[PDB]
Amino acid sequence: SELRIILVGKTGTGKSAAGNSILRKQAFTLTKTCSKSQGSWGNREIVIIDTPDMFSWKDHCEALYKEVQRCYLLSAPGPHVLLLVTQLGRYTSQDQQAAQRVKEIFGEDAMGHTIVLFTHKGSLMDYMHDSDNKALSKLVAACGGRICAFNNGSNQDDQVKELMDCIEDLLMEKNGDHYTNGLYSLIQRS
Amino acid sequence: SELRIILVGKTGTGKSAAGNSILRKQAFESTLTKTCSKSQGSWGNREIVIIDTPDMFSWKDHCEALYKEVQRCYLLSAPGPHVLLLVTQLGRYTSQDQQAAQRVKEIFGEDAMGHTIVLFTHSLMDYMHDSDNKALSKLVAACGGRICAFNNRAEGSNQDDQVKELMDCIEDLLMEKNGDHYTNGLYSLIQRS
């Protein structure tokens, strides 16, 4: 009864650190390859697939295509949730590019399983309300307003609980179904 | 002892028709090519396997379908191509052909040019010397001067001659490569998937 999470985001958002917080272990310099770590939270078995920083970059190369294939192989038969990790008050073209790559790598429908994570160091809804960023508003609306703040002990357990609550809410809405596409179906036959 | 050929090129270069000429059969539909196709034939004592790729490989953007077709291409051409035929139209090398060449490097790796032969669909050295396109010369130099002219409407004896001309280029490349096919980390990943 595993829960598969794909971490996506630009360099310096603390993507790997958020994965280590969820698994409560050192499960995961630039991230150059996909990594997979297994852990738990409560009664739940959690599988996290960390992706390279280059997923958020503009260009393409052999390594990118290879890592898209590993991501698919490591997250097969599909992710339950895609965590788009971004930094509070610092949503730039690089974050827009990372969001766009989620749609290009997994299909437009992947946004239906995406939660936007806001890393920093109620109060989040206060900043969103006054946000003058048209691109960020477009992303949050595309992710059905599924947003969660995250500061990267007790306070750490609380923000994981907050995020696990978002994830569970999405899962309940999806009746526990993971996201899938034609490439996942192709892997499943081969 | 099969010989694997991947066909790459922009829309309208007669990419599928060249594949059909090499195999001497209607192996591929020659509309847009939307998916990868594989057809087998023979030449001499060698089995020729041809992997036709979508026109979108020569396009600027990326999508789910492109990543799916990259995977099929890799699966159909595994453990790797001996040769990549970059099909271009003699007298019409544009930014779209430059993009197709660039995508060979992005899909298969920079070193892939080392296994690439430029096919000119339509004396060829005469049209080459008449050309003043700097981008095209840069591509031909990147492909070690491995160029070949092709008439996709050629039949019988003339058809056999242009395949022989191309098979000569391929054999020259193969000798240089010591019969080795081109490979990368993604072909290795597919092979163990």
Image (tube, coloured by chain):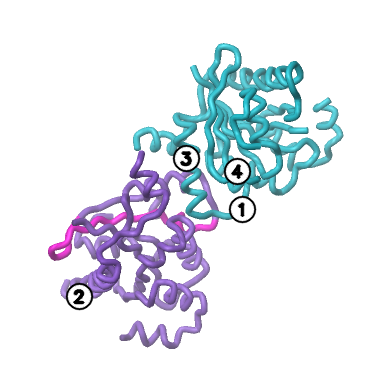
Chain colours: A purple, B cyan
Callout 4 crowding tier (Cα within 10 Å): few <14, some 14–19, many ≥20: some
Which chain does the residue under circle 3 lie in?
B
Q: Are marks 4 and 2 in contact (CB under 8 Å)?
A: no
Q: Is residue B112 above or below residue A109?
A: above
Q: Which residue is mark 1?
A: B60
Q: Which residue is mark 3?
A: B72
Q: Which residue is mark 4?
A: B33
Give the label, 3 or 1, closer to the camera: 3
Q: Of marks 4 and 3, which one's residue comes earlier in the chain?
A: 4
Question: Tag 4: residue type?
Answer: Thr
Residue at 41% x, 66% y: name it.
Answer: A111
Which chain does the residue under circle 1 lie in?
B
- The span picked out in magenta is A39-58
On the rendered structure, is B137 left or right of B22?
right
Give the label, 4 or 1, closer to the camera: 4
Q: Residue furthest left?
A: A43
Q: Is residue A56 magenta?
A: yes
Q: Is residue A135 above or below residue B16?
A: below
- Whether callout 4 and callout 1 share a subunit is answered yes
Q: Secondary structure at mark 1?
A: loop
> Relative to the observer, which residue lies in front, B51 or A157?
B51
* Inter-mark Cα distance, 4 to 2: 53 Å
